[PDB]
Image (cartoon, rainbow, N blue to C red; front, side):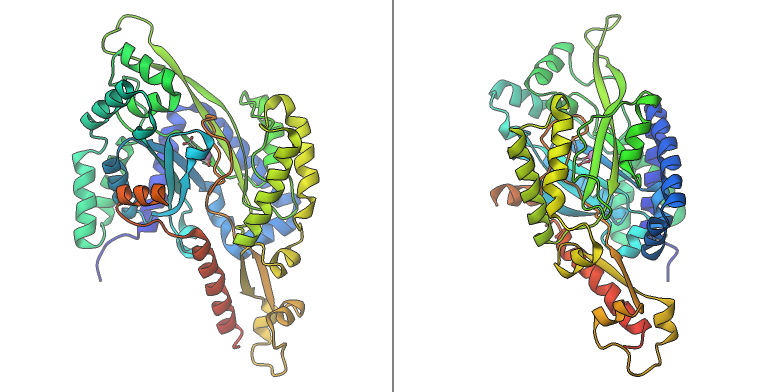
Length: 450
Ligand SMILES: O=C(O)CCCC(=O)C(=O)O
Ligand code: NI
């Protein structure tokens, strides 16, 4: 037909380019990647069941480069335009996170691909928050932020041209995709020179460090990039030795044979300097960049997430409120005890409808595909070894803040306001998981001549 490259391939290239840029800016991220690779190879060598699970789902091939990014934007126009940028790469808005509950003036979505085959080529996802200036009570500070954000243009003209070209023509060829990746990178690069005066930065920062992070810079720099490890417990044991001691509180469920959602922790990655126009030849302020690591397990159904939320809430009530480093050991013990009630058996997770799964025809099943008298049900085919299943991996967010901006774990006027700013409706991640499960069953039925 045409010579356009796949949006999935652009996404993979963009993720790799973002990772190279971030590693140049934050060398301890490179240190983390080396540790992740070694941990992951150890798991696959020592745990054949994990290696086989990743083979069945195709995740073995996506794992090494799998990342998420997090960014914050300041205006509705920025959010709507960034949705168009991400669409070039097959990254659509999935989910709505209203973080005003946890005491942060933002609401968010995650831009990512949605179909198992797309995700196999690249599962790159960018959690994108929009600052809500109307939640800044001090009028003078809100007016300052609005004035500063209105002046900035976070996209290069060439990036905007290529986005419009992609929309009008239906894609980009390889050369234009390469140009697009490099132009898009400018939006996310770190810029030391703040766009405000030293005093303006001071006012923005004391209200909330997140407000200065958004308002005082040229654009939405990478807040962090997070690689995927197969064993967060193991990586935590290796991190202090590399100068990235992480938080003892691990967000998410406790250690499980069959992980659910994701587990996360964070560390201090770099102390950065911020420079101002009015105070040159003088010491500029400093700001910390935080890193993160995650392990991704099974996507949960509504019923599964209700159980997860219940047991996590019970853990927090038993602790007395806020999990902190000072009570980390007690919290982790309470977490393990309360989550004993969440089945840690794939067969029960499936039969009780707690997680999503993908199903696959086995070699034994394929060899029998012309036999009569085979089992008449899905369970019978599983029991006879004709169908194999594995959990469908979670692609979304608890969410958690590496920089400690909000309390962890979350998910109509606010949603309507978000979607009006975004320019479209967010997709339902749970519906998308159900569709992936259903597609696997249909492919299995065809492969087995059922
Ligand atoms: O912008 C932030 O502070 C955190 C964004 C959410 C996130 O990255 C995660 O859940 O891993
Ligand atoms: Ni993150």
